[PDB]
Amino acid sequence: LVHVASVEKGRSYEDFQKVYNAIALKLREDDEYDNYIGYGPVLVRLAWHISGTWDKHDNTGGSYGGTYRFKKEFNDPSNAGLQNGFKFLEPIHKEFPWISSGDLFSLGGVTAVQEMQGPKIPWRCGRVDTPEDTTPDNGRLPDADKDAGYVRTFFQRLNMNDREVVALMGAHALGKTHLKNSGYEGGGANNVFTNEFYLNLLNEDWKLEKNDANNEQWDSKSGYMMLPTDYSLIQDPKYLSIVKEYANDQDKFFKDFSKAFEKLLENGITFPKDAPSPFIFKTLEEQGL
Ligand code: HEM
Ligand SMILES: Nc1ccnc2ccccc12
Image (cartoon, rainbow, N blue to C red):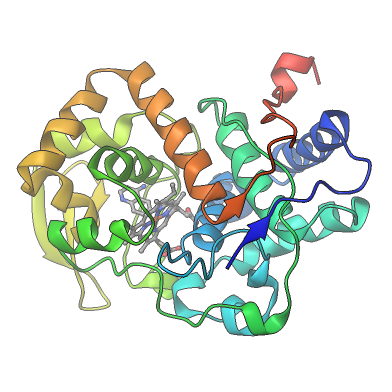
């Protein structure tokens, strides 16, 4: 199964920076969402979940087809709460009806990471909407109540190795869990992209507790939390080495996250030899906007 990137007809970097800017300006404007976290974190989660359905074995799922717009995927229990991201992006899609759904969902994640002071993430256009029958079945996204071996095996399906997995997980610096979406309780409000996930893992005094949904999670006296799968990164000695690396080198973390996240967002897509190079969008701040 081959999905060839096809540039939206006549579009170039200027067109996609306008979309980026629209997203970024709305991220600034809609600041109250989720007790003033804003929409940045849920857009990152959205970009991940629309990509994380990919299966390297048969090239089903992935970001290319924009299949999250279909009920079966929109209603995946693993996607609970992402409707807020979809609703945020609707007026963007209305203004720029030419951009494909996959392009919009993935670009929203890139925009969010960058506007939250994250690394620059190169981004390629050309995802094409595919029909409803291409929507992957539920159950391809990962469970949060398992161990390092599960995480490692899970991510093999997405062609991610240990460093890619650990880097990608650093997005859990952002936002929080919501009991009504996932059964995990969190109390953070972070919407600045940093390596603090790794620092918190290593520095806090974690206690294994049960939350109000009767699920186990790791909690600290300071008020922080980790999912079982998060905590597994310090239980497994190979992941632990990488955690320590990123805790001690912000730039390395940014660089490896950027690479892994672009890869995640591009899995499944064949880019023609003469496709445009990846775009690196300027932030609002870099543009003086
Ligand atoms: C083993 C893999 C992972 C598991 C089990 C997992 C699980 C979770 C869960 C349970 C939530 C809470 C959802 C809610 O209650 O609203 C969450 C949120 C989040 N996840 Fe992950 N995740 C994984 C990997 C990732 C990856 C790879 C990224 C992106 C690079 C990502 C980005 C996020 C973000 C940004 C949020 C916060 C969303 C918000 O504040 O609304 N996660 N994840
Ligand atoms: N903010 C967070 C801290 C630790 N784990 C998380 C897991 C999912 C979302 C957010 C977090």
